[PDB]
Amino acid sequence: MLNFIPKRCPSVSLLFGKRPVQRIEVGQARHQLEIPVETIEKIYEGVDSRLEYHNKDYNAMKWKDFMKLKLDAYHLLEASQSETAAKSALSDLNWFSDLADIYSGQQTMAEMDVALKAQGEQKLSYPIQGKNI
Amino acid sequence: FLDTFTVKATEAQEIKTIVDKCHKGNTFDFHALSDEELRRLEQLYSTVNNRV
């Protein structure tokens, strides 16, 4: 991809932010994809306005942000190309132990907040030979 | 019959006179003041309630 972000002025991109969504066609099959206008507006914080190309209709991003974007694309692409890729793009999850521990803890705390109530044990009546019989 | 669906007075007397009241009086408070045979008393529990 190029570092050419269209100017959002209406003289260049008519009707940029009139609605809260943008749409694009992707690939040879031209799959549709909808993107929030806020996700798109995130780019215009990195956009640099000193630089203007192609009839002064496209600005350039800062190289840090542009290359971050490129690296994210490349990572997604190579994950798509590989078979052993780490599905579940979320990173190393390590909070299943705490969940198990709190589950067992609540279970036990209920089990032993029961038998404080279910063992008042006022008195008992044991039948004993010679006396109760 | 009654020896199998009731507790025996000898079993009663044994613990009543040797185990329980030797601990403490007015309320029979706690049980750390005792021998290992408290475990036997526990076994006695698991006999008595499991015959009655």
Image (cartoon, helix red, strand yellow):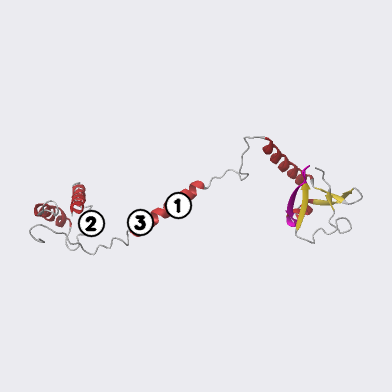
Q: Chain of mark 1?
A: A
- Going by the numbered disc 1, the residue's amino acid type is Tyr
Residue A85 in the image, given as x and y percentages of width and height: 63, 37
Q: CA distance from mark 3 to mark 1?
A: 14 Å
| Marking on residue A45 | none
Quick one: quadrant of the N terminus of chain A?
A: top right
Query: What residue is shown with label 1?
Result: A103
Residue under mark 3: which chain is it in?
A
Protein chain holding label 2:
B
Crowd rating for badge 1 (residues with CA inside 10 Å; few <14, some 14–19, many 20+): few
Proximity of marks 3 and 1: CB atoms separated by less than 8 Å:
no
At 79% from the left and 54% from the top, the residue drawn is A44
Foreground residue among A64 and A36: A36
Give the Cα distance between marks 2 and 3.
20 Å
Residue A28 sits inside the magenta stretch? yes
A63 horizontally vs A75: left or right: right
- Image height check: is A26 above or below B25? above
> From which residue to which does the magenta span run?
A26-38
